[PDB]
Structures are given as structure tokens and as C-alpha cells.
Amino acid sequence: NTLLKTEKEELNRRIHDQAKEITETMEKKLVEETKQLELDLNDERLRYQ
Amino acid sequence: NTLLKTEKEELNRRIHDQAKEITETMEKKLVEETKQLELDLNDERLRYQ
């Protein structure tokens, strides 16, 4: 009965870790998206000059 | 004795999910580095022309 309580302490810490690292993955994902159209219009930009 | 075995199934999947996400976020993270100098050198470039 003690070790599944220590395991309870153990899995709660990492489902929350998953729910901060996945938030980081999402936070970086729209940065990936925003930089994708950023390099697109700069490649177009120097072409015209 | 049943449910800490079902918990064992749960935690093994969840640490591997963390380890797959960790290699994905690292795979993204070095391309953060590559796109950081990619935007940089074109600022220098269209400026010169």
C-alpha cells in the first residue's frame, strides 16, 4: 500500500510535466508557423530588387 | 495487487510518450537554431542591393 502512493506522487508529477512540455510544443508550433510565412515573403522580397 | 500492475502499464507508456516527445522537441529545437541564422543573413543581403 505504500509504493502505489509513491507511484501516485510519481505519475502526478509527470502528467503535469507532459502538460507543460506539450504546452511548450504548442507554443513553439505557432512560432514555426509564423516563421514559415516570414521566410516566404523575404525570398520574394530580394527577387524584385 | 491488480491495479498497480495496470498502473505499471500506464507509467511505461507515459515515460515512452515523454521520451518520444523529448526527441521530437529536440528535433524541432535544432531547426530553431538553423532558421535563426536563415532570417539573419538575408537582412544583410537585401540591405546591400
Image: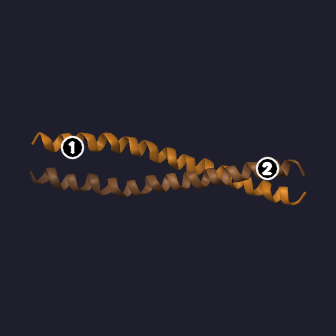
Chain colours: A orange, B brown
Query: What SS does tag 1 mark?
Result: helix
Query: For residue A29, what is the image quadrant?
Result: top left
Q: Tags 2 and 1 in contact by the CB under 8 Å rule?
A: no
Task: Identify the residue shown where x is 37% and y is 58%.
Answer: B33
Task: Identify the residue shown where x is 24% and y is 39%.
Answer: A41
Residue matched to label 1? A43
Nearer to me, A40 or B17: B17
Separation (CA) of disc 2 from disc 1:
52 Å
Query: For residue A43, what is the image quadrant?
Result: top left
The answer to whether residue B20 is left or right of residue B8 is left
Query: What SS does tag 2 mark?
Result: helix
What is the x, y in percent for residue B46?
15, 50
The answer to whether residue B17 is left or right of residue A24 is right
**Label 2 vs label 1, nearer the camera:** 2
What is the x, y in percent for residue A28?
46, 47
Local packing at callout 1 (Cα closer than 10 Å; few below 14, some 14-19, many 20+) is few
Q: Amino acid at mark 2?
A: Glu
Residue matched to label 2? B7
Task: Identify the residue shown where x is 88% and y is 60%.
Answer: A2
Q: Mark 1 belongs to which subunit?
A: A
* Count of numbered badges drawn on the protein: 2
